[PDB]
Amino acid sequence: DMQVYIANLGKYNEGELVGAWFTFPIDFEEVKEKIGLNDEYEEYAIHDYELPFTVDEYTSIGELNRLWEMVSELPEELQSELSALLTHFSSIEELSEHQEDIIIHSDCDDMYDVARYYIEETGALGEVPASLQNYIDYQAYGRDLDLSGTFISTNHGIFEIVY
Amino acid sequence: DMQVYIANLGKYNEGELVGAWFTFPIDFEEVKEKIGLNDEYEEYAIHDYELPFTVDEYTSIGELNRLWEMVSELPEELQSELSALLTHFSSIEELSEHQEDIIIHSDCDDMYDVARYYIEETGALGEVPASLQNYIDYQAYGRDLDLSGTFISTNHGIFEIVY
C-alpha cells in the first residue's frame, strides 16, 4: 500500500537483486543499510512500485517524500481517483492549487442525473412548474453541460472541475 | 357550387334523363315545371350533387333547404372542412350546437407548433425562463396534448374541439 522496491544502482547485472518494501516516510540511511551499497553511494533503483500515480525510475527519494505529503493530504475519494484527475491536470502540485474547486457528485452517476440535480434540486435556470416538471429535456441539457464545462466520470460519482 | 341534379322518379328507365342544376333555395314548383312529371307528383331523384357534405338519394328537398341554412351560416374556414369536422361530430345540427367551441389555429400547422403556441405564447403551464426556454421538450408534450384532448389537422390550420 503506497510503497516501492528501491534497490539498487549497484549490481547492474542484478545477481540476487535486493531491497524489498519501504512505506513513507523514507530514510536514506535505513534503506541504505537494508540494501547495502556498491562501495559508494548510488542507490534508489526504483524498479517496482505501488502508488496512485506514475513515477520514473530515476526519481530522487526526497521528491517521493515531497509528493507523499500532498497525496496523503487529500480525502479518500480524491485519492481513489488521482489518475482520473491527472487526465485533466498535469501535476500533484497543480492539483493542490485547485483542490477545493473539484465538486463531487456522490449521488449522481451519469449526465442525466447531473442535469436532473442542477434543474430540480438547485433551480439553476429558475423555478420549475409541476406540469412542466416532466416535460423538460435533460439529455440535450446534459450534452450542453458537457460541452460547456469539464466533467469527469468515475466509479464513485462525478467530478466537476469548476473555474 | 353547392347544387344538385334532381330529376326524376318518373322514367325509371331514364330515357333522356332530365333536370340539370338548382342552387339554393329551391322551389318545388319551379323545379317541377323545369323537369316535368310522370302525370303525378313523384320527383327529386337526387342523382348527382356537389355539396360539402354527404346526402342520400331519397332526401326531401325541405331537408336540403333546412341543411343549407346551417351550412351557409358558418364561416368559410369551417365550410372548407365540413367533412373533417364530420369525422368527429355526427350531424350539422350537432355542429351548430357547438359551433363556437371549435378553436382554429391558422398560425399553427403541426403539433410541435401547437405545443410551442400553448407554452411560449400563452404560458399555460407558467412562466418560461430564457435559459430553460430552449430546453423544453415539445414533442412529448404535443403527444400528451393529442392523447388528452381532441385535435384535428387540416390544410388551413388545426381545429381544436374543446369541452
Image: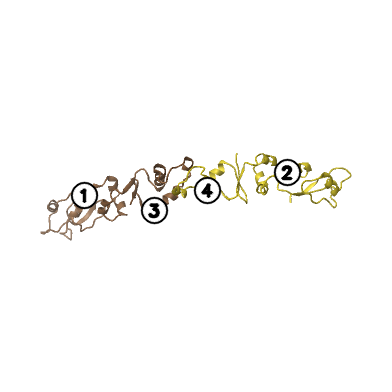
Chain colours: A brown, B yellow
Is residue A52 visible in the rendered image? The answer is no
Instruction: Give A91 or B5, whichever is nearer the viewer.
Output: B5
Chain under disc 4: B
Instruction: Give B74 or A27, whichever is nearer the viewer.
Output: B74
Distance from disc 2 to disc 1, alpha carbons, whole Å, reads 94 Å
Distance from disc 1 to disc 3, alpha carbons, whole Å, reads 34 Å
The crowding category of the residue bearing disc 1, from other C-alpha atoms within 10 Å (few below 14, some 14 to 19, many at least 20), is: few
Give the mark nearest the N terminus, 4 or 2.
2
Distance from disc 4 to disc 2, alpha carbons, whole Å, reads 37 Å
- Residue drawn at (42%, 52%) of the image: A144
Disc ID at residue A69 = 1
Q: Amino acid at mark 2?
A: Glu
Q: Which residue is mark 4?
A: B116
Disc ID at residue A148 = 3
Q: Which residue is mark 2?
A: B69
Q: Is residue A142 left or right of residue B109?
A: left
Q: Nearer the viewer, mark 4 or mark 2?
A: 2
Residue B66: x, y in percent? 75, 42
The crowding category of the residue bearing disc 3, from other C-alpha atoms within 10 Å (few below 14, some 14 to 19, many at least 20), is: few
Distance from disc 3 to disc 2, alpha carbons, whole Å, reads 64 Å
Q: Amino acid at mark 4?
A: Arg
Badge 3 and badge 4 in a common chain: no
Please identify the residue farthest to the left as the structure is shown: A39
Distance from disc 3 to disc 4, alpha carbons, whole Å, reads 26 Å
Chain under disc 1: A
